[PDB]
Each structure stands twice: as structure tokens, then as C-alpha cells.
Image: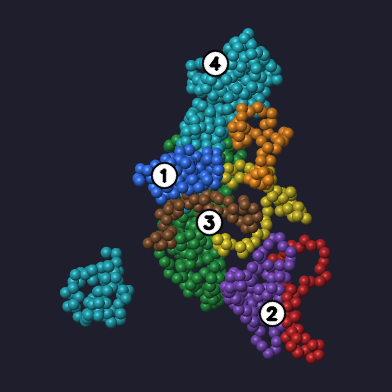
Chain colours: A green, B cyan, C purple, D red, E blue, F yellow, G brown, H orange
Amino acid sequence: TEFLKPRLVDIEQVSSTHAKVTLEPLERGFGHTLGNALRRILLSSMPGCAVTEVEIDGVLHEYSTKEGVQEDILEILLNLKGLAVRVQGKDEVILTLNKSGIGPVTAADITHDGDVEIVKPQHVICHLTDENASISMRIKVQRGRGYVPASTRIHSEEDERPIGRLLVDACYSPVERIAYNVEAARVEQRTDLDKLVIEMETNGTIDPEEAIRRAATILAEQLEAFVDLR
Amino acid sequence: TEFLKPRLVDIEQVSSTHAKVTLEPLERGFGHTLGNALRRILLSSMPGCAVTEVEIDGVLHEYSTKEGVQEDILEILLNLKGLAVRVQGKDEVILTLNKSGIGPVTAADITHDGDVEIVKPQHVICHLTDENASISMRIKVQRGRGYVPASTRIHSEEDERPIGRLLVDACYSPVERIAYNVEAARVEQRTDLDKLVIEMETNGTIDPEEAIRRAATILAEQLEAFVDDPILLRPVDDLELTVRSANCLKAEAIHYIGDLVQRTEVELLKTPNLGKKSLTEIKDVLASRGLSLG
Amino acid sequence: KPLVGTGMERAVAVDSGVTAVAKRGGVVQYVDASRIVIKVNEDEMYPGEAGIDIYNLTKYTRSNQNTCINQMPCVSLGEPVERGDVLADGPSTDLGELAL
Amino acid sequence: SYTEKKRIRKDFGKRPQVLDVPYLLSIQLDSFQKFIEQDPEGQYGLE
Amino acid sequence: ARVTVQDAVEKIGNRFDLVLVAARRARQMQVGGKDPLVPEENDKTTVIALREIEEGLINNQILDVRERQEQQEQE
Amino acid sequence: EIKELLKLGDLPTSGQIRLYDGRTGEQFERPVTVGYMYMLKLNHLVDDKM
Amino acid sequence: AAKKMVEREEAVVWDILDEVIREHPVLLNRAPTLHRLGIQAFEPVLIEG
Amino acid sequence: NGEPIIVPSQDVVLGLYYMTRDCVNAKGEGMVLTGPKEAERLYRSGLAS
């Protein structure tokens, strides 16, 4: 009847993607329970932003080649699917990208708006191998969770798109790998209190304390239906 | 980005100590999360009072034998472990048991105190084979959380262990058995959502739904630290006007549809060089823009 | 590519004709999604020509089993090549190794 | 080599190769060569 | 008998005429619209007929005397 | 030589690591052989068989 | 109208299909039927896939 | 024959064999249990093997 509450004490931010959040203290056996519940919730359902539609000019479908560029439109779409981004204010932003000359067009050349920050700026999208070449696209960034493939998005929409609106599979989840280790915390009168360190590898577009806050909120709002009725 | 909450559809009372809850629908991969969390909490850290120690007189240790009783002292420790007490006052109550004669001793013959009570008075402790034989034991209960066995209890207990004492396991948590399983459910189209079917079978001193509610209360209390004229003011030259009708409407000195809305049908035909074709050219585009005039 | 292989993969991938091997070595003048333009060395160049080879990559051609055939260029701009190296990975080859 | 300097496969074979693997389509190309080719006396194919 | 019909076989004696009498009762419920003597529980007429057989409300001669008394009360 | 390369890569020599359960969070009682096979996707697809 | 309703796969059509499938056995067979237990009746569950 | 055909095959069999094997000093041997529900509780909590 005398349980103690855990406290989010430190976030050892190792790199822009890595993290190490330790919760302390926990009673005997609560470490594995809270660690596995938070690991399942954080790996499954965390909201983030991803690319949904791209519209390149002069390109009618993904299975086509552009002159001047080096990679196909399928390769450009997979490279844009790999792009991580952070949208602050709104729910859906549309980005543009115009670049000419010879050289790898990166994610730094995407013209930012106010409430959108590109986290990994050196991320390469395409390669230009002509002096008179140019590409101009309209990248659309949505926000959801989980994994919504483009075929089931065509299943789950209503209108017809114009020809030249390439759809991308959506992987909104920012979290890639989460492990937890339960050591024994050192509280001077208790030889049973554990600490739970959640090493977590994002893709940069989320904060670790924010993620564990959202995960504990999801777990509490799911346990509401148990704690209320029977 | 809001979630899906379950609708409880079943509390199937098998008996007064065995229910079968069923929650559906839950999000995909949440049935195992909630079920394993509640199962680990109920097995390991649900507090409740149980027998931890018995001092039976005339018996040295577990490999001796008292007479007049058809059960060995291993069976006596087992039957005493199976008893279901509920202490309301204190954290430590030492009971006594005294009964002589031919016949079995039940839990109704236990010398009760005012605080504790026995939910199974018919729970048999022993049987007696001799009329002159008697039973004389002190039974110590405590308050604790979850199962903790007498093997590690006596491995940790290295003091002067007096004669007559006998370690027994602690069935502190009131649940005798919980085993969920996760089915597959289906909101109106999709079937990746799941249905969680808890099959809880406690002992007495609690209801199953009460223990499930207290387990969820334990988990929520443990988690609650980090828990929380729009188109009229637009220009007119992008409304598919031809190169003749453009200089027709610029003779009307009009740049916005906000400068067309006040233009009455008398003005539309008394202003110069707006013929019938230009009248149709402005009329069909105001019709396709939905606005009316006059 | 397989992390565990045999070394027969490069032989199968070149000898199948499904890649684009370099007829005469030199340096790469211009890469595209559908063209490779190689400036030949003057030693391999013949005394009556210019020394420019064009490779037209076949893109998204259908195979007999309705699968995809396209040649993805595996060289970069200004990279020097020799006679007998892979310029374009075929359908299921990776840098000139068989990758099924 | 140039396409081999970019990724070299670690070889675990302990015996040398005194004969490389030949051109794997010599059978078809050589048979149709002997059919279609102009020979004077060693009579092959169309002649 | 939504799982197994061995109890209805134990009631009648022979699975083949069990199938025939259950078919006749299911036709009387599906075409004729006669009342299911067992509660429905939102079931198909074949499983309602097998439930009636396993309960032991109808048989072959019970169905024959039922349709005979319907023929007597009409004609 | 396989074990020598495994010792270079700071991995277990016997080839087997200790895996944890994905759902319950518990641990499989024996070490499980974990590695990197090369899988192929054959042309007998349920889109064509169904 | 019924053809367009079944062809468009409305949610009411899926509810009707779950009502129809219910207590309607299907036969499952795998060639070669070497003996009689290579045809067996099962009750179907409607699964995505 | 008269033998059953609904027989467990290799994974049910490996699991039931591994469940009903025996060790000599596994974990918490020599305890005395009130029954199968207590044995299930012991193994699931992890106080025994």
C-alpha cells in the first residue's frame, strides 16, 4: 500500500537521434511492467510527420525517367519517404524544392516555412548531372501515426487526383528502436528500488520527454476503462 | 490523432470467485499491453494479508510427526496456506487453534479475534484420529504484497529460529489464477483491432472485478507523475475572360467582383460596349462562380 | 547483394548480358537515368573516330514473366572506368553482383 | 579493377584457381556461329 | 448442435435418417414458416432443427403425426 | 573461421544470443540462433493463386 | 441496385455477408483426395487477406 | 485403422515435451504446492522453473 512514484530525472541526449531516459524509483517487478508497456506503446503509436504526396513537373508517373537527373522517380520517391521533418503549428504543410546546376540536391535546399523544421539537413534526395537541368517539386507533409500505405489511402479517399500526383507510402512513426534495462537504484534505506533506463533511438523529429509523456498519457487513458467500470 | 476506447460487454460470473471480463475493441497490439500489465501487477504486487508462520507445539520441524492426526504436517502447512484471511485492523495477528476429540477440525473452530474473519469457515485444516489427541498451534499472519516463498524467506531468515516454528509460503495477493487471452475483434470494417478476454479466478476476500479495478488503480496511480466577401475582393482577370471582353469590362472600370456586386442589371446594359456575347461571357462565369446579380 | 555468397555472382551477372558492360575503357562524360556517355581513352581509340560511346539503358521493359526489367546506372559523373566493368545494374543485380 | 575497388568480397577459399570460369554462353553462340558462318572447306552450316 | 452432433445421433440412432429428418424440419421452418420450438438465438434453420432434434421435441414419427394432425385439422 | 569472425565482431561465439519476448516482455528460456539469411520471393503469389 | 450495392461493397453488404456465412459450412479439399478425410466441412471465419 | 487422425504434430509435441520434462536443480525444487493454479502462478511470476 506504500508504493512510490517514479520521477523523470534525466535525459542523456547522446546524439540528435539517440536518448537515454531513466525513470526512478520503481518497486520490485514494476520495472519490467512499465518498461514493456512503454516500449510497446512507443514502438506502436507515436504521432509524427511524414511525406504523403509529391508532384514533380514534367513527370506523369513513378516508373519514368527524367533527363539531367541521375536516379529514377521511384528512387526519388523512396528517398523522400526516408525524409524526416518536424511540423510545429499546423497539421499539413506543403513544401517546394527548386534547384539547378550540377550537384546533389539535398534536404537543405527545400525552402522552409515558419512552422516546419527539417531535422537532418544533409539528407540527399536526388543527383543532378547536367548543367541545364532543373527540378521543381511540391512535397506534401501530413501528420498521423502508424503506417498508412498509398494503396489503402486510395481505398480511404473519395476524390480523383490529377495526373502527376505521385503518392508515397506513409511511415509517420518517429521511433525506430527502444530497449530498456532495469538496474537497482541506490536509495539509502531501500535495497529493492529499481531504476528503468529507456534507451531510445528516434529519427530526430521528436523529443524523448515528450514521447514518454504521450506514452504514459495513452496508457493512463486506456486504463481509465478498467478503473471505472468493473 | 485520438485513440479508441473499449466497451465492456461481459462479466460472466462462473461463481463468487471466478469471472470472465471481455473488453472490445482495443487498438492493435494494446490487448497484450494491458493484459500483461494487469497480469504482472496482480501476480506480483497486489497487497493482501495471508498466513506466513505457524508455531505448532510438540513438533520440532517439518520432518517430525505429530500423532492423532491422519494428515502429516506437510498437509497441515498446505491446508494452513490455503486459508483465506482478511485483517482489517493491524498488520500482524497471531491466532490460536485448539480442538480435541474424534473428528475433523475446520476453520470454524479457529479462535477468532475481533478484527480478522474467515471467508471459508468450512475449509478443513486437519482430521483427528484419536479422542484424547488435541491440536495446539499459534498461527501468525502478516500483510504483504504478492507471493513470496518460504524457501527464500528462510534463506533470508538466519536469526535464532525457535522450536515449534514452521515456515510457510505467503499467498498475499488475493488472486489464485489470472490468464488473459487476446482474440480478434472488428469495428465496422477493419479487423486488426483486438478483444481482450481476462479469465480471473481469485480466492475469497475479494470479488474479481474489485481486484481488477484495484489493479488498474495501482497502475494509474503509479503512472500519474508524468501524465497530462472572400472571393469578391479577388481580381477578375482570371475568370476565363477573352481578349475582347477584357477591354469591354475595363471600360466598366471594374477590377474586383466586389466592384461587380453593386453593379445593377441596368448598369450592366447601359455601360458602353457590353454586347450580348459579353453579357453571356460575364453571366456564365458569375453562374459558375455561384454569385448572382441584380 | 548477399552477405554470404560464392563469387560466381559477378560472373553470372556479367555473362548474362542483363547489365551494361563497358566495351572500351575510359572516363564517364555524362550519366543520366537512361543514358551513359563514356569518353574513351586515346589508346583504345581508333585513329578515324571521335572516341565517344553511348549506352542507352532499357527502362521498365516487360519480361516474359511480366516482371520488371530496368537498368539502373551504377557509375557517377567523371568516374574512370576500364574495359569490362559494369555500368548499369540490371533487374536483380547490385554493383555487378547477382542479387535475387 | 574499378567496379571491384568499390566493394571487395572477402574470400574464404583456400585453393587457387588455375582456370577462370569461361564465358557462360559459349555453347549457344558458338553453335550458331558454326551454322551461320562462311567456311571454305571445313563444312559447317549453310555452306 | 453448433459444434458436434453426437448427442443428436445418440438421440436418434442413425446419422443418415437424422440428416433426412433435420432437412424436413428445416424445410418446414424455412419454406412453411412453422414455429421453432427451441428459442432461435439468431440461428440458421438447420441448426435450429438440429437443436430441436437433440433436445428431443421432434422425431420422424413426431414430424409425421404433426403433419398428419395439420392435414386433419385443415381437411 | 566462422567463430573467428564472430569473435572479431564482438558477438557470441556459439552463434546464439538471448532473445526477449515481444509481447509479455519476458525472456525465452534458451538462447536462440539469430543471424542473417538471404531470402528470396518466389513467383507464386496469392494475387495469382486466389 | 442490388448489383451496384454488392459491387461497391457497402458496410451493410458486409453485415449481410457476416449474417449469411454464419452457420453455413464450406467444404475444403486438397488434391489428391487419397482417402475420404481429404474433404472436410468447416465453418468459415471471414478474415482479411 | 481405428487410430485417431487428430494428432499433435511436432510443435504441440515439442511444447508438451518441454513442458513435461524434468531437471534436477532447476529453480525452487522441493516446494510443496496447493495445486495446479499455484504452480501456474509460480511459473508465471518466475519464482520457479
Quarter of the figure that contains the C terminus of chain B:
bottom left
Q: Secondary structure at mark 1?
A: helix
> Mark 3 belongs to which subunit?
G
Q: Amino acid at mark 3?
A: Gly
- Kindly indicate whether the residues beneath marks 4 and 1 are on one polypeptide chain: no
Query: Mark 4 or mark 3: which is in front?
Result: 3
Q: Is residue B276 left or right of residue A199?
A: left
> Mark 4 belongs to which subunit?
B
**Residue B291: percent from the left, percent from the top?**
25, 68
Cα distance, mark 2 to mark 1? Answer: 93 Å
Query: Mark 2 or mark 3: which is in front?
Result: 3
> Mark 1 belongs to which subunit?
E
Q: Is residue A86 left or right of residue B137?
A: left
> Mark 2 belongs to which subunit?
C
Q: Secondary structure at mark 4?
A: strand
> Of the numbered discs in the image, which one, if any, rests on residue A17?
none
> Of the numbered discs in the image, which one, if any, rests on residue G49?
3
Are circles 4 and 3 on residues that touch, CB within 8 Å?
no
Categorize mark 2 by other alpha carbons within 10 Å: few (<14), some (14-19), many (20+).
some
Location of mark 2 (residue) = C23
Location of mark 1 (residue) = E67
Q: Quadrant of residue H49?
A: top right
Q: Secondary structure at mark 2?
A: loop
State whether residue B287 is above or below residue A189. below
Location of mark 4 (residue) = B110
State whether residue E49 is above or below residue A158. above
Residue at 48%, 59% in the rendered image? A152
Cα distance, mark 4 to mark 1? Answer: 68 Å
